[PDB]
Length: 30
Length: 21
Image (cartoon, rainbow over all chains, first blue to last red; front, side):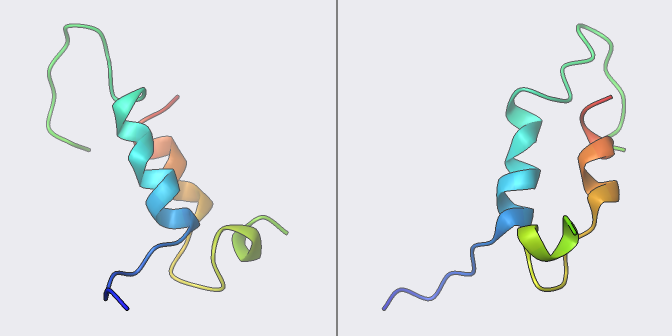
């Protein structure tokens, strides 16, 4: 069994793909 | 009851607001 923790939080974080666009405005990941 | 749905712990709703509106 491969050791890797996976949960809803992981799915929730994965949102950065569609979220965090802020268009062309760049700002620290926060 | 959304916190338990995501995980039993180590999971907060406040985390979604970090990247999305």
